[PDB]
Structure formats: structure tokens, C-alpha cells
Image (cartoon, coloured by chain):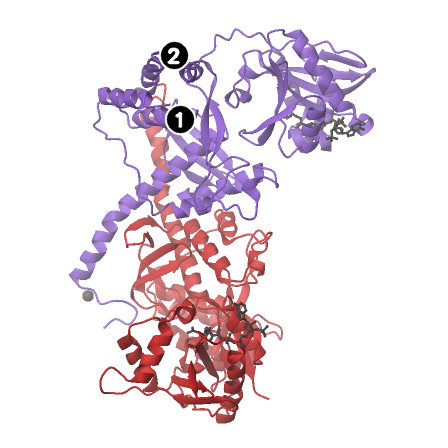
Chain colours: A red, B purple
Amino acid sequence: HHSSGVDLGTENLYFQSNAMAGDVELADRARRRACRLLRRWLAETHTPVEPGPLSLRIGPVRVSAEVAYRSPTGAHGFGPIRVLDAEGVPVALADPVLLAAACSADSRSRSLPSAPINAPDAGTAVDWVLSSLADDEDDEVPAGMTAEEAVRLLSRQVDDLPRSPGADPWSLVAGPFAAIGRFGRAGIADECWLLEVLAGRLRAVDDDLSRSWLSSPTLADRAVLVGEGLRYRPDVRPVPFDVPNPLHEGKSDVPPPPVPVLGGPWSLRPVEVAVHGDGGPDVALVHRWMNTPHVAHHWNQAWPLERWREELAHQLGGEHSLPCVVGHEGREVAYLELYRVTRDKLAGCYPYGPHDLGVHIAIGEREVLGRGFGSSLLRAVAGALLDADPRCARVVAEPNVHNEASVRAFAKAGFVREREIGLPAKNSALMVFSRV
Amino acid sequence: HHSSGVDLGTENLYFQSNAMAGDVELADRARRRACRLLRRWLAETHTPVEPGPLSLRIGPVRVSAEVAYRSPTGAHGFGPIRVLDAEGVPVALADPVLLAAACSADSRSRSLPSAPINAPDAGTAVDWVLSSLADDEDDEVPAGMTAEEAVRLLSRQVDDLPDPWSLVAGPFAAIGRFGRAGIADECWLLEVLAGRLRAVDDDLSRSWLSSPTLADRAVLVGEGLRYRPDVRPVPFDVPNPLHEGKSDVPPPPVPVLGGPWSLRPVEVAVHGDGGPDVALVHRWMNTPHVAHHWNQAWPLERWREELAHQLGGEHSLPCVVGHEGREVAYLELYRVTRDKLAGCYPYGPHDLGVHIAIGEREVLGRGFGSSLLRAVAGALLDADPRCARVVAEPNVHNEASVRAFAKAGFVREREIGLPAKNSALMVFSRV
Ligand SMILES: CC(=O)SCCNC(=O)CCNC(=O)[C@H](O)C(C)(C)COP(=O)(O)OP(=O)(O)OC[C@H]1O[C@@H](n2cnc3c(N)ncnc32)[C@H](O)[C@@H]1OP(=O)(O)O
Ligand SMILES: CC(=O)SCCNC(=O)CCNC(=O)[C@H](O)C(C)(C)COP(=O)(O)OP(=O)(O)OC[C@H]1O[C@@H](n2cnc3c(N)ncnc32)[C@H](O)[C@@H]1OP(=O)(O)O
Ligand SMILES: [Mg+2]
Ligand SMILES: [Mg+2]
């Protein structure tokens, strides 16, 4: 009767409808995976998240979703994750493997070509995700759970952290904190309150690990999408990285960046923003420098003049960043930002000491310079900062691993490349100039 | 007022609803994409399709979908495409990028490490799919279209043709979309198309009406595929729906080998354990070098049932080859017009193929194989004077067998995509 299809009876419709029943749950399962990946991408890239629209370039795709619930531990709750074309039209929903592809494309690109993540036998997060679709579905948190019972689970879990000398430091983030986020995202309890409770369970035992977890400004977590050392042989061989420690004070009495005094051919002074008019010649110099191509290619801050005026005034009015004009034998040639790490984005990336100072650098008169200037200046600045503040342990910097002139200039000046770090727009070599 | 969320007013909900309105359309577009990809995969691997359930291995995932509409041109209509775990439970919906990833893995593996598809710089179908998400999507066939307008548009399109894959990619594509839309029966539209080809007597039209295969362009399967962001497709042969062969082709003949060689059909005894021949093949088929390639290291009863099945039909003829009195190999001699190979190259009706396993290479693996292949081919060409070719389809990865065939006078003509493997189409031609 039918040649291009099957002849239909009610029994056939019954069979197919009991199959299409479960598709709804299959839909939710993909949503949860994609939500997990995005949480990781944001965590491993130290991308700031706040409620409302989140908009994000990840590899080759514009990505956008509503942050319905912002989580203190990073367990954000998302609206539909959508893919956008160049002008904001949604073109797709971000399925788990679509994200795994965008992130793998983005990550492999963030790291250097010679990195392990880019070895031919290395595999990709796509392989990892594809391989795990049949894996066991973790129980989501029962919506009716009581905060009382939530604390009971957390206290029990906290007390089961390895009383062991060689024990995993990511245990705290991967065990208890993960639970806290699932509790908050489920609407079961406020995560700050749960964290406060966990601090209490940690204070009760003065174990070495317990006390450091209360005192360190960062904690160990494990990355699965961002990091030069990643492999996905079949599954992921994750790599450790530092995330902010929520159990640790949010401001301190650390004074602003000092104004160092440099040796040799170098002069240094803070920028001055005139309150009258368009800002003055210092604002003009930075604006001009920051819009030249060789600078803008790395800083990506080729803004209009008034935007730079407010930035410099903004920095100068605070305790974070100190913008400076550097001169070489009387000619003004470079711009610096010297900043307190404890108030910078870098503070969530490595175990900083309270007085750490960092530097951003741009040589603006590159129309003539690239002749040993940067490394000599960088060296002077580091020793000069260590002289200005004897409670500072390190001067640090975050050049893009691809910014090969900056990285080499930093190391010629005596910085040591400790590790790669994932930042929102780039992966950076954490260069460290250490005291004595 | 809320610390971890946004304070909601009705205006915020309005903004979010015109977004979720379009989400439904975002779902269908993924569905249309995934169905387009699966159509290509099935075509380019020559995987057989009939209505009802289709179940299929693609790279690292079991894949399963209902075939609601079986298309003469391959534009099949699917239910939900689902991914299944090892014991049949669905675990995911086969989203478009998921498919391109599984197919990329499967294809890169099917082709040789030296193939362009496997170069470090080649890019992957994943790159191609992601890069095209932002494309403006081609319009669907107007659901209210009349069959007349279907014919009018098709005739106009046929008449504006000159490349050989122009037919499958132009007219057949429309027939597939017309059919899948329910506008007209594809068999009727294909018949109309045939007439418009008779109307012009040029070599091009005549070949299209007479050849058992047509040229199509592949985008997932092929040693030569490149994805410089965009895909650089490669040609392959698909079955020709406009062709049905007069056929009347007899079963495979029994060749007579010269020199040190003897050949005879297998015998399967009734009621016992199949006799001694069923045992010898089963013994051979389970030794490591044989099972490593044939993947037919079965128990004894499946081979009894297997060989009996072949001998009773017009497809395959199982034979035992002896060399100077020692039985040393197993052959399957088969008619191409009845084999999986018939959708893969422009076959002649009497073409014959051969599968071979040398079981006593563990005692007689010393240069014999190519020489036996040479004898068998010429003896088959003697047995069927209407046969044009002897062919074989070893896995492109089985380079020892390929080399043995070419030493015996077969030519490695092309790579072809078969349901489980890519094969070197080795051809011994009477020319
Ligand atoms: C917010 C932010 O953007 S974070 C701030 C970090 N960003 C930056 O530092 C980018 C600033 N852009 C610039 O152009 C910077 O002024 C610089 C530091 C990168 C210029 O410094 P330079 O004048 O080039 O210093 P210098 O001449 O000493 O260069 C040192 C090394 O760079 C290497 N180098 C120079 N150019 C290149 C290049 N194109 N590729 C690779 N290495 C290079 C030089 O060979 C030298 O190494 P060497 O010891 O073997 O000779
Ligand atoms: C579904 C299916 O079953 S697909 C059917 C196709 N069959 C298969 O895929 C599996 C085949 N399995 C077998 O065991 C096959 O019989 C073989 C061909 C692989 C056995 O044959 P062989 O014993 O290797 O024959 P032979 O040694 O002559 O091989 C000839 C090739 O090897 C070389 N060779 C190797 N040893 C010798 C030798 N001792 N003397 C001369 N030539 C030799 C020949 O020069 C020739 O070409 P090459 O130099 O380019 O490699
Ligand atoms: Mg019916
Ligand atoms: Mg409200």
C-alpha cells in the first residue's frame, strides 16, 4: 500500500510516541552539559560574570545567554545559550558538542603552537565530550531539600576531606564548593551563608590544610578546557589552576602603588589629568600612543580621547593603578601602569602576596624604538619598585603568550615564566620578578 | 533588590519572550541541518536505507532514527535522530555539530594516514559546520506548490544543463525536495525527467540515461576532502535511479585454474555439523590474520548456515583453493550486480568480484597470493565471455592485499565508500 514509508496502525504510533516521550529529557540533558561547559569556560578564563546579559566571543562564534542566577562559587544559572551572527541575529542553540568545538577552537588558539594541547596526538575537548555522552547522569539536587539537611551534607562532606599530608588541594573546590553551588542554583540555600558555615567547619580543626584554606587568597581548581598542558587521550587529563578564594577578606589596608625613582637614562612621573578642558597633553600623548597600530594590536585600547581622559582620572583617583610617563634621555617614549595585584584581575589567578606590584608597558615611539629599550626599562622599574616598597615580594606581569616581544623583553629583564594563565581575552605568561 | 539576579518587571519578560519565540525556529534549523548531514553520510558510505528504523555506527557513537520517507534520490525524511548507548538506551539528540564530529572521526579513520583529509593542515567538517552556522539558509520548498509547477520548474532546470555531477546536484536535488515536501511522487518526477533527456540526443543525455551510476559530490567521505573553512568536495558514484538493467545475469561461474592450482565449490552436508568443508573455513576464518581482516571469526554453525546460504543463491559462490594438493585458501566469487559494490562504480552486468583469505599462510605465505589472484581472474574471464571485469574491494588500509592484487594485474582505480570501510577498488579488466 505504501512504498516510501511504513503502513500505519495505532500500534506503530504507540511505539513511536513512547520514544518521543523521553526526547524532552534528552533535551534537558544537553542543556545541562552545555551549562556545565560554559561554567568551566568562564571559570578557567577568569571571565567576570554578573546578572543579566552575558555576551561572549568563543573561538569562531558569538555566544550569548542571560545570567539568571549569578553564583558565588561559579555555578551560574543560565537562560538559553544562543549563537549569534556578526550583527546579533541568533542562528543556533549552543549544544554541548557545539560548545566543545568552539572552546577547543578558542583554547588551542589561546595557547602557543608548540604547546602540548596542540600536539598531533593530543586530542580535543570535542573527543572528550563525544566520548562521554553515554556516561552516568549525576543526580541533580532534590528541590525539596532543606537548608538544615544541606548543611548536614556539607558538614559531613567537609569532614571527609583527606586528613593526609599528600592530599589534593583542589579537593575543597571540587568537593564541598561544587555542592554549595548546586544547592544555591537549586534555590535551596544562600551560597554566602553556606560558605560561612563551611568556614566554621574549617576553623574547628587546625589541620595545616584546613588553616591554609582559610587564609590563602586563592584555591586550587582543575581546568579541563583552558591550559597548554591539557590532553584528551580518550578522556581529559586535567591541569591545575588558581581561582579566587571566597573564604578570604575582600579589601585590605594595602596602600596605592608607590611612585618609584628609576636609575640610568630613565625618568618616570605620574600622568596629570587637567580638570579643565579636554585633559591636557598627558591625556593626549596616551591617547595618541594607544591608537597607533603597534600598541593597539596588543592593548586593544584604541579609544577616543575622552574615554582615555576618564580612565586616567579614574586610575589616579584610586588605590589600584598608577599610570606613568617614562622618558629616555629627555624624550618621552613609554607609558606604564603600575598596579596593586590585590585590586587587579591578576589576584584571582595566582597565590599573590598582599603587596605584589605589577606592570603594563607600551613603547609609543616605536616609530623609532625596539632596540633594547623595553628590557632595560622593565629591569629598572622592577628593582625600583622593590626599593620603593620593602613589603612587596614580587613584581609581576601578564603578557600574552603570543606577544613574543613582550615576553622576551620581560625575561631579559630578569622575570621568570612560572606558568601560563587563562585570562578573559588571552592566555598569558605569568612573568615574575622576585625579591632578593 | 536581588543580589544574585535582576529585578523583574513586565518589560524584562517581554524582551525575553521575543527571544524564546524564535528559539523554536532555532530548533528546526538544527534539525534540518542534521538531516542534511545524515543524508550525505548515508549516500557517501552507500549505507542501505529502507522505511522504518535505521540503526547505524558513526565513529564513536551508535546513531538511530526512524525513516519516515524513503527517497529514490536519497532525500529521506527522518524522525528524531538519537544517540544510543551500548545497550540501546538513548542518551542524546544528534545535534548538527555532534554529527559532523562523529562523521569527521569516522571519515578521517576510513582514509589512509597519507590522505589529504588527514593532513595536519586539512581542517575538519567540524570547522565547516561551525563556519556555516551564520549562513542565510536556503528556502524550503513552498508547501502549497502544485505538481504542475513542480514539473514546470524541473523541465526548465533540466533544459539549462550543459560537468557530470550537474544532474544529481541540480535536477535530482529538486526531485528530492519536491518529493520530501509531498508535492509529487519522485518516481513520477524522475520519469518526467527521463523524457526531457530523451528529447536531446547528445552524448551527455544519452550517458545519463544508460549508465547504472551517476556522479555526485561528497562532503564527508573521501581521501581528498579539504575544509579550508569551506568544503572542497570530491566526486563519487551513486546509483542511477533512471536505470534498471535488463539483467538476466546467471550465478557466478566455476572457473578452472591452470598450473599448480585447483578450485572447487564448497559442500555443505545435511543434518550433521556441516561436513568437513564448513569446519575448514571456520578453522581458517578464526585464525588471527584472517579474522583481523574479514571479521568473520564466527562459531561453526554460523559458517555452516553462511555457506549454505551463499550456495543456494545467485550472489556468491564459496570455493576451496588447493595448491599442489594442499588446500590453502578460501574464495568468494560474486556477481557485482547483486553485491554492495553495484552502487559504487559504473558496473557492467556480468562483472565478477573476489574475496580471498589464505588460511595456510601460516605454512604457505611465500609469494603465492598474487599469483593465485592472477590465475583466478583470467579463469573467470574465460568462464564468462560476457564479463568485462574482475574486481575486488580490499580495505584501503589493507595495503598488503592491495599490493598483492596490483602485482596480479589489478589496477587501484579509486577509493570508494562502503558501509563499514573505505576500499581500494581493484579492477582486472579485459579491456
Ligand atoms: C593591558 C595589556 O595590554 S597587558 C601589557 C603587556 N603588553 C605589552 O607589553 C605590549 C606592548 N607593546 C610593545 O610594543 C612593547 O613596547 C614591547 C615591550 C612588546 C616593546 O619592547 P622592546 O623595545 O621591543 O624591547 P626589546 O628591544 O628589549 O625586545 C626584547 C626582545 O623582544 C624580541 N623581539 C622583538 N621583536 C620580536 C618579534 N617580532 N617576535 C619575537 N620576538 C621579538 C627581541 O629579539 C628581544 O630579544 P633578544 O634578547 O633576543 O634580542
Ligand atoms: C570482505 C572481504 O573479505 S575483502 C576481500 C579482500 N581480502 C582481504 O582483504 C584479506 C586478504 N587476506 C589475505 O591473506 C590475502 O590472501 C593476502 C593477499 C593479503 C595473501 O597473499 P600473499 O601471500 O601476501 O601474496 P604475495 O606475497 O604474493 O603478495 C604480493 C605482494 O607482496 C610481495 N611479496 C611478498 N612476499 C613475496 C614473495 N615471497 N615472493 C614474491 N613476492 C612477494 C609482491 O611483490 C606483491 O607486491 P608488493 O611488493 O608491492 O608488496
Ligand atoms: Mg494504514
Ligand atoms: Mg519583580
Q: Secondary structure at mark 2?
A: loop
What percent of the width, then of the height, locates residue A88?
Answer: 28, 55
Asked whether residue B87 appears in the rendered view, the answer is: yes
Q: Nearer the viewer, residue B90 or B28?
A: B28
Q: Nearer the viewer, residue B424 or B83?
A: B424
| Residue farthest to the left, as pictured | B10
**Which of the 4 image quarters holds residue A252?**
bottom left
- Which numbered marker is on residue B201? 2
| Badge 1: chain ID | B
Q: Is residue B27 left or right of residue A383?
A: left
Q: Is mark 1 within 8 Å of ligand 2?
A: no
Asked whether residue A204 appears in the rendered view, the answer is: no
Q: Which residue is mark 1?
A: B166
Report the Cα–Cα distance between label 1 and label 2.
17 Å
- Residue drawn 58% across the image and 37% down it: B111
Q: Secondary structure at mark 1?
A: helix
The C terminus of chain B lies in which quarter of the figure? top right
Viewer-nearest of discs 1 and 2: 2
The N terminus of chain B lies in which quarter of the figure? bottom left
What percent of the width, then of the height, locates residue A390?
Answer: 51, 93
Q: Count residues near mark 1 (Cα–Cα under 10 Å), then give few for <14, some for 14-19, many for 20+.
A: some
Amino acid type at circle 2 is Asp
Q: Nearer the viewer, residue B11 or A271?
A: A271
